[PDB]
Image (spheres, coloured by chain):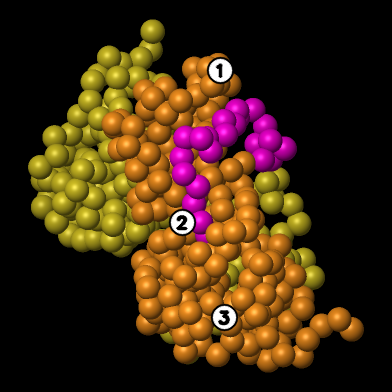
Chain colours: A orange, B yellow
């Protein structure tokens, strides 16, 4: 009754973070809406996702910049996100009134894999603070990070969207927005890709401010930098 | 009282599957046992894990062959594992008395990422059966695979060790051991790595049949093939 007969395919390339926490609700709304649209989703590295859209068979890249690198893709900012610190309750950090980055760097760290899903913002942060991060555990998944934090491997740094006190009781969470710069999740595709109505639809559903009018305009800019500044006077979604 | 004062480091490179399901209990037993041993664990692709041990800073590669590719690593078989089919209960497969591969290939598939964690055994299987797999979703993580299966993207093929009816109620599981050949998880390191007592200890704890005597012998074989046939007359662990 309220579905579309639109026929086609939607091939998306994304990371674990998006597919796990950002995507499922959207995809559910989409697949129900567009039954004759075959949906594909393939997890890979920022470099692999790039390839898949730049050279391969993917329609859309959904990743935190970079990327969707470069460059030679139309990039549209979707939302901002940052990190939380996860530890065990008898950890020293859990008992420190306000946690600085210096107090954090005294400890072994459990976090995302190199380059990354917001790791380079972490390393940049440590460099800027004249500090050396003791990285003990790297993984793509926030689920494994929690496990190893739970058994005492170290301090966990993950996306805040990957934290749930009802799904993760007993791990203490520490908001670290004033420790790390935020990350921007973006969406993109080749300039030659014909934008179907279900494509705009998916886009707007993932990023509301990305209406068909601003999407076509952004395409016409021929610059992902000018697309970014397009939204500098509004507040992007935060997750 | 029952711990060791042994000082050193254990740098391991593995996949999501091992770190999530095979590793945590072992690591927990290890870290408690060897407090002055700094433990590292880094998730990556079979090729990245190889590099890390062949050229990088990793001590041990823990991965399903390949690898731990090649070759130029000492490879020791740890255990055998196979796949299960996960679907929703009103799925046609869930209602088919005994599921063949042909009946499986009629459906969109949700599984591991290319090359892989037992995916090439899947593709080989389909090739052998003169069938074309409709791969819709690839991921490193069995957790995301379940989610997308749950919302109806397709049929899930995962490691059986990643299935738990108490942790995953309402997804029906289909044992597919007679559909796919099993996979062998292996462990390895450079010939030049000095084997510490905590290293043998970790090894034997991950693979009981890998005692210090069979480990040193395997090292002396100068062939990972001859190491494999060493255990052809015993039954390796199955998970």
- The majority secondary structure of the magenta stretch comes to loop
**Mark 1 or mark 2, which is nearer to you?**
1
How far apart are the alpha carbons under marks 2 and 3? 52 Å
- Give left or right: position of B154 versus A126: right
The image position of residue A54, as x and y in percent, is: 39, 79
| Residue A167 locus on image (x, y percent) | 69, 40
Q: Earlier in the sequence, mark 1 or mark 3?
A: 1
Rendered image: mark on residue A217: 3
How far from the left and from the top, in percent, is residue A201?
Answer: 69, 77
Mark 2 touching mark 3, by CB under 8 A? no
The residue sitting at the right extreme is A1
Determine the residue positioned at 74% across, 83% down: A35
Q: Look at the image and give the residue range highlighted in magenta.
A: A164-187
Q: Is residue A180 magenta?
A: yes
Please give the name of the residue rendered at 51% of the width and 83% of the height, measured from the top-left corner. Answer: A220
Question: In the displayed structure, would residue B125 be above or below residue B203?
Answer: below
Report, in whole angstroms, how far the alpha carbon at label 1 lies from the one at label 3: 47 Å
């Amino acid at each position: 009754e309220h579905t579309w007969p639109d026929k086609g395919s939607l091939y998306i390339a994304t990371t674990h973070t998006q597919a796990r926490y950002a995507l499922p609700g959207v995809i559910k709304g989409f697949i129900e809406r567009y039954p004759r649209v075959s949906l594909h989703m393939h997890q890979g590295s920022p470099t692999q996702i790039a390839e898949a859209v730049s050279k391969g068979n993917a329609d859309f890249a959904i990743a935190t910049e970079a990327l969707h690198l470069y460059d030679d893709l139309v990039m549209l900012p979707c939302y901002h996100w940052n990190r939380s610190i996860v530890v065990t309750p008898d950890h020293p950090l859990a008992a420190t009134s306000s946690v600085t980055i210096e107090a954090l760097a005294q400890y072994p760290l459990v976090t995302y894999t190199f380059g990354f899903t917001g790791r380079s913002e972490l390393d940049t942060a440590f460099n800027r603070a004249g500090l050396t991060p003791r990285i003990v555990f790297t993984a793509t998944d926030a689920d494994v990070i929690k496990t190893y934090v739970r058994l005492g491997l170290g301090v966990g740094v993950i996306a805040s969207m990957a934290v749930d006190p009802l799904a993760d009781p007993d791990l203490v969470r520490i908001d670290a927005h004033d420790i790390f710069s935020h990350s921007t999740t973006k969406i993109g595709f080749r300039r030659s890709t014909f934008l179907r109505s279900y494509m705009y639809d998916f886009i707007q559903r993932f990023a509301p401010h990305l209406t068909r009018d601003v999407v076509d305009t952004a395409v016409a800019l021929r610059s992902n930098e000018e697309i970014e500044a397009m939204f500098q006077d509004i507040k992007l979604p935060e997750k």
